[PDB]
Length: 49
Length: 231
Length: 49
Image (cartoon, rainbow over all chains, first blue to last red; front, side, top):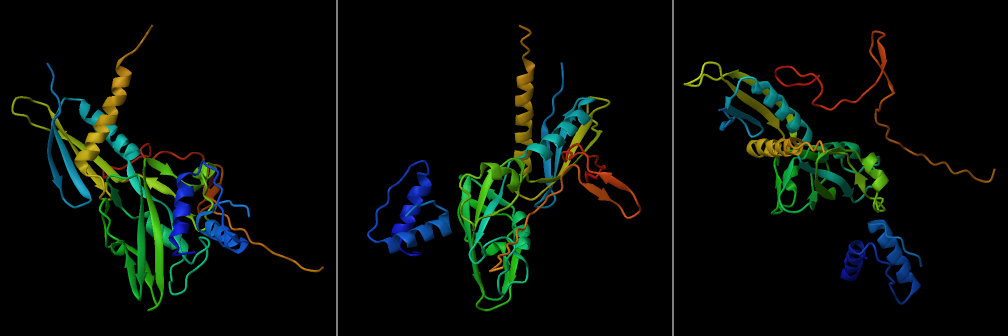
């Protein structure tokens, strides 16, 4: 979750559209937990799984 | 039938210390202008300074890194003194990455175009281990006055990243101001005075621009005063 | 008692009006006002007290 450019794009878009609710779809729950952890520990984004 | 002051020679003794002279000042306006400028300079000069810092291996201000001897708080204290000139943008992100034994000074910052690091010799840290490495990203803003972290906490605006370390902002470049009004023998006049403004700054604002901006602000407010409705 | 969890909070308190300050000779006082830099007295050289 440090070099995959998709994550940086997601963060950048969210931090640039902070006033928008965004629905993000992934395949499996494990990847969703990793995404919550990275958005929290490096941008503090509130995300429910 | 009046006189009016013209900006004359501006001696620069050092990079930080400067003398500015104003020759043709009418009697009595010497002290008035001296004090007004001193006030405006000390109070209202806009500058840029670091607002918050994120270092990698550190959760909070009070922990400690391996291979450094200063505490993190002292690192913030060192960052508070960094004198920087930003030209175009309002918020810049500087990146510091250094490894190995040595003093990490301000010079090691990655050289960007729009940002000028005034004092590259300014020390930041001392490493003590070959494999010890520090990386950090310092966010620098423009502002006026003095704003501490704790007041801005009301307006957090998603301070959510726990890695964020807020620093108090001293948005003011001028350290010291003195002035002397002394007799200015003008070839066709008896009793005229010249004002000499001696100024000490952190080396970001140039003297000419400081004086011009101060005069601008004072003239604008005085303009606001000139009209009186009485309606 | 099954178990206990202790948590330490650290808080940075800055000086503000109303705190008590003293000297070594028995002189006391309450900090009454924070003045702007410009208002404070200054010697000819420009250093404020």
